[PDB]
Amino acid sequence: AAQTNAPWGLARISSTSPGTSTYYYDESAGQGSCVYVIDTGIEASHPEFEGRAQMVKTYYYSSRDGNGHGTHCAGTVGSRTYGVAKKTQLFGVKVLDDNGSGQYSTIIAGMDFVASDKNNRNCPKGVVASLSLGGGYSSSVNSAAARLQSSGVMVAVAAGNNNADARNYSPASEPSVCTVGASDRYDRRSSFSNYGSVLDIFGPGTSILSTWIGGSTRSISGTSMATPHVAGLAAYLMTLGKTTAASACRYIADTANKGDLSNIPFGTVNLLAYNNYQA
């Protein structure tokens, strides 16, 4: 399949080269997989989601996304125009309030929610969790992310936007999950992107156009938005049978575009998520 005039990030993940605008992907498109977006919620009613998005859990007075960040990430995972995996199922877990903040314990509870809730869902191709969130180092948040990974969910987490080593942030520093940095459309490390040996992969993170609340769209930047690209890619690759939740992060790194990013500090991987689709 070919999506002309796609957002640059979708076009990048199906390209050996920057500077193209068509997204190429197998039509299976993540059908029969599921991605949990653990964030501020999802505006499930957004026409971009086509009935494939639903809120399954909230820790606040409302399950709606009053922020837009979770809606934006869900749109990059699986919205019809802005999504990597245009047919996956999206499950919203609102661990962040509408200011975008959450107590870690609510975040931990939400991760443990996903690790059980996936047994209440039909995801025969497998389960992904996109965690576009983070804060300071926490061994209890790291371990919640490792449990989620261990339960059979590919976990993809933001490296963080501090331009520092990700070892001082959680769940970024958890080694068992898939820690994602951010690149820009010129194949540069995003100026805000964390780095370090704990990063597994980079995805498009600068000026990412996706769904927003109120039925709108907008372009925003963050290792937060690189993560749903990898999360959407994992769901896509799992539907194609190319990998499993336990080995997806590593499959993605094996098959990534290698050595193409600039301003990648010594010791951090120079790998850019790539779907390797041959049209």
Image (spheres, rainbow, N blue to C red):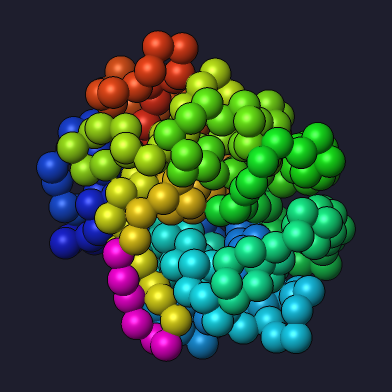
Where residue 262 sits: x, y (%)?
25, 24
Locate residue 171, reporting x and y percent: 68, 41
Could you tell me which quadrant the N terminus lies in?
bottom left
Q: Which region of the structure is painted magenta?
A: 214-219
Which percent across, then down, holds residue 7? 25, 58
The one of 128 and 168 positioned closer to us in this rendering: 168
Q: Residue farthest to the top?
A: 266
In the image, what residue occupies the spot 77% across and 54% down? 104
275 sits left or right of 70 in the view: left
Residue located 64% across and 46% down the image? 135
Q: Which of 82 and 2 lies nearest the eye of the viewer?
A: 82
- The quarter holding residue 175 reads top right
Q: How many numbered marks have been drawn onto this rendered protein structure? A: 0
Left or right side of 221 for 124: right
In this image, 218 relative to 104: left or right? left
Magenta-colored stretch includes residue 150: no
Q: Kindly tell me whether residue 237 is visible in this rendering.
A: no
Q: Nearer the viewer, residue 74 or 25?
A: 74
Q: Is residue 217 magenta?
A: yes
User: Seen in the image, is 30 located left or right of residue 273?
Assistant: right
Q: Residue placed at 78% from the left, 74% from the top? A: 59
Type of secondary structure dominating the magenta stretch:
strand
Q: Position of residue 226 (x, y in %)?
A: 43, 47
Q: Is residue 31 above or below residue 262?
A: below
Is residue 11 visible in the rendered image? The answer is yes
In the rendered image, the vertical position of residue 83 relative to residue 232, given as above or below:
below
